[PDB]
Image 1: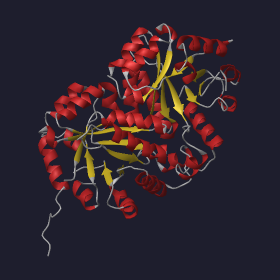
Image 2 (image 1 turned 180 degrees about the horizontal axis):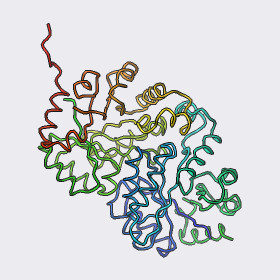
Image 3 (image 1 turned 45 degrees about the horizontal axis):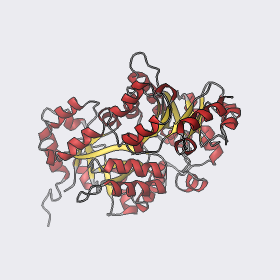
Image 4 (image 1 turned 45 degrees about the vertical axis):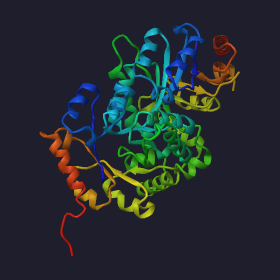
Length: 224
Length: 231
């Protein structure tokens, strides 16, 4: 049974509590929150939620020098989170320090958060990759490069498009998490067949008439 | 007029309060905190500090899609900080959104935080630039390109090394902040001479036997515009 993660887009604790109350029992609920929430809420907000049993993909895409990311990651791990992201663009050493940091901050009797690398953000078009980022390679090649390197450096997985998972998965093998966002009922069943380890789903659930029923139905479409 | 910013590399509010007690009157102190502190202490600690009159460079290097950075940046401007960072590698639109977010989150009356672009981190060597990040440009060209783009995208300044200021300035000009961290008694004097808008200083101050006097001496050196007589 592979996890379905609900992507949340909200900017306060109150909104967060409200959607979570609509998603189900805490143990059954895996959500993604980024900096729009984390930078707007008290430091103990995530910790309180993970104490209750909520699983949290805290998506802050850390991108700094290795020693600072060691310490950032370490601080995050003490929140009780399940997944977290770094930019592969920050390089091999930074990624390794990120994992060492996660290990260091994981409190007794907890699983170490999984370290996921971001490659090229979805906001990066072909033109931006070439003319703004001054990359030497086209998209498909840049992405595979970063993902491979992330795997070599101690990342547990990568955030990748559902339409890349096939070929990424071919290259890097089964010992890695391929976490695919942008899934809509690219359906959950297609993501399963193409090799996704976890799907991230937003509005189809969060904007649903009954977010809980939507969330539960996607899990079944993903795991049937 | 030109700021000296104290880099605080610590992970707890109690150690923070101790170094701060030695830096002087809050209205005379400008500090830099990054992931290490912020991800342990959170927003209340920053709000507390800025309300007292501390100037904070909150250095979190946001790097995400434009809409998310808009909201991240907006969240940070509510805290009353002075400088904050984003990755130029995140692209032109992300930088513009960051600045718009900063504007939206600033309380009325208050001053909009300055948006500073990170270019290539000091952790990226030429080999890392070439063979990990798959850049097609050599370091100096890539740095200038990222800096120029940041200027054209609403950034108020860049983080660069003291030595880089001249090339960046030559191309970008005076309506921009060149913020330079490597500084130790590259000296404050050299940083001044080379056109740094602001320096960040760490251990030379935070581990000095008298941090306040080390700080004031560096402010003085950095701002010695007419150090020598000339006619």
